[PDB]
Structure formats: structure tokens, C-alpha cells
Image (cartoon, rainbow, N blue to C red; front, side):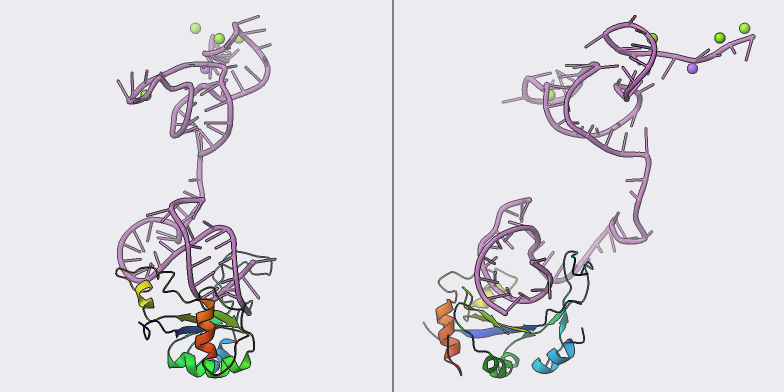
Length: 140
RNA sequence: GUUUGACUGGGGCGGUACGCGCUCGAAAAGAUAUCGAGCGCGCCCUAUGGCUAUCUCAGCCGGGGACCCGGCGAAG
Ligand SMILES: [Mg+2]
Ligand SMILES: [Mg+2]
Ligand SMILES: [Mg+2]
Ligand SMILES: [Mg+2]
Ligand code: NA
């Protein structure tokens, strides 16, 4: 049963929602791979009327690139609880989000016969705290 | 020397139902009138055309009315 039910980290998105950049540079070094532009939608008063327009960057890290990052990111954060997803996710911080899920996720991300992951096989906030807390730190 | 139009609950004044498109009137095929009700067109676009690749939207919810992540979401 287990082994295929035990949590794992799938991508950690580090993004800097600026309002118009030079910031990529640090993201590249804090993570280890190129950043991606962040265009914005809708015209608004914060002199942000431009639809297509660089207004920040993000970086999606997977596997080791994500651990080797969290092995310093987490330590720089304290928070826990309430600040967790209903799907077992949590964002802290410059933002650093951690998407967590179990082994059969590809079923909902592939092209052919894709399917949505059953509520039971989903990751709960609690089942999430456990996994992570059980990895160099403490909850709440 | 001539012209100075037509429609019109008489004619004039007002209006254009004088060329066009849609809903209703219209009676569950088609056709269908009034100065019938609601309202539009006389353009604009080198992309706002064409194809291919990749992709899924509104709105709401939860975590850090811009941006980022997850979820619900046949279509508003
Ligand atoms: Mg004569
Ligand atoms: Mg005369
Ligand atoms: Mg007459
Ligand atoms: Mg008919
Ligand atoms: Na005439």
C-alpha cells in the first residue's frame, strides 16, 4: 500500500512579483537555473496598463534542484499551519511555494487518458505537515 | 423654357416604416401588413486575414483587486 502513498516534493516555484527585471539575476543564483518572465493581464492604475509586459519572474525547480534549494529556504522560514494548502501545499517568504503530492500524479498531468486525482488519493494539510516536518524542522 | 419626387388614418408641418441586417409581432413548415415594439448597417482590420504548435476561459475558494502555486469550474 504505502511507498506509493508517501508524499514527495513536486516543483518549488520561487517567484518575485515585481511591478515592472534586474531581479532575475538573483533568482538564477538562489536556484541554479534560468528565470522566466511574468507577463500580466488586464490594464490597471498602477501604471500597469500593458498587457504583454515583463513584471516579474519565476523558477520551477524539480527533484534535487528543489531539495538543494529547500535545504536553505525552509531554514529561513518559521511559519506553519493555517498557512498550508487544502491539498497539502504551502507558500512562504520573494515567494517560495512548495507543491506536494503522492506517486500517481502523472495521471493528471499527462496527455493521454489523463484523469483527475481522487479526493482520497489527494494530499491533506496534515499528511503534508508530517512529511515535511519529518524533514529537518518543526510544524507550527 | 422648365423643374420643384414618393410614403402619409386628407393635405401641410414632423417623420422615412424610400437601400440594407437581427429579435418579437408571425398563429411550432414556408409566406405574411401597419407612421407595429426593441435596435442596428453605409465601416473598421496587413491583422482584427491564413495555417501550425502549444494551451483553456469567466467567476469563486484556499496559500505567499498586480504576479506566483493549488483546487472547484461545459462555458456565465
Ligand atoms: Mg413644352
Ligand atoms: Mg412653376
Ligand atoms: Mg401625395
Ligand atoms: Mg413560419
Ligand atoms: Na423629381
